[PDB]
Amino acid sequence: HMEQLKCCSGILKEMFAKKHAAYAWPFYKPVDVEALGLHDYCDIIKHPMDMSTIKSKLEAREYRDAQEFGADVRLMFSNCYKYNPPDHEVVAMARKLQDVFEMRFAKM
Ligand SMILES: Cn1cc(-c2cc(NS(C)(=O)=O)ccc2Oc2ccccc2)c2cc[nH]c2c1=O
Image (cartoon, rainbow, N blue to C red):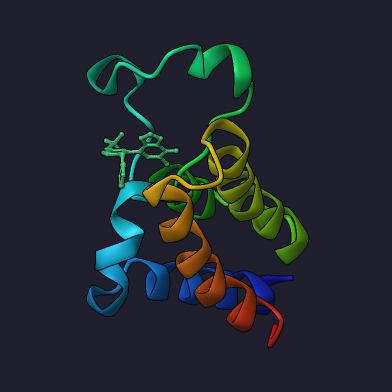
């Protein structure tokens, strides 16, 4: 699984790339519930996730395989779709970033 984890690190680096920043930036770090004033975020989202946490987990070798890495990336997008109304701008941004992830993750 060392080779598939190098691919996971490559995919995450691509998600942080300048060419995707216009839609990736809300996912770079944890949702700051207090600063944003997000009503009941912690009641609705039991397992928050973001790209910096995923990066820290890859560096600490916490994912034993590609499936575990992919589960955290999809959790990050799922939390966004779950919390927000479907018409929210952040949801449209999550979909664009998920295009990047799914298309590369499938080429594992
Ligand atoms: C994942 N996410 C993130 C934000 C969000 C986060 C931060 N900065 S941060 C990472 O918290 O430090 C800044 C703005 C944010 O809002 C917008 C981002 C773009 C367009 C409209 C809203 C958010 C807000 C409500 N829902 C969400 C959500 O689900």
